[PDB]
Length: 158
Image (cartoon, rainbow, N blue to C red; front, side, top):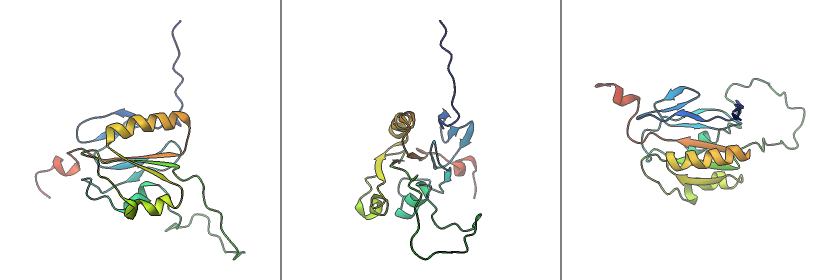
């Protein structure tokens, strides 16, 4: 009667919390990161909940509509219209880590226009909700932010 836990590698989950970092896939990121079950891992140069801009929200969404280095170069045989991914974060979980920074329409509208529902919470609250939405199997991306420490605190100089 021992329940076998069958691990699906599509479930990108935090393997260890830690102080000054967050361990995902046993990769201990000592800085802000945005990752999803289906999606990329965005590295944030954010150290505090004050660094968060609309630009960074676009990065955290893992969109990248314009590719800096096109892997599949289209010579453009058409000039009508393009089809967007639609695999974008249906819900975006922004975790400020230290304290909830209320992001307003000014910053979140660029994503709201795409249908991206942005939640403003902290790392802990975002993690729980992320697990729910990831278990549900919905397009969710979570951005977690260090709650006090970072790579900088490992040094005593710059």
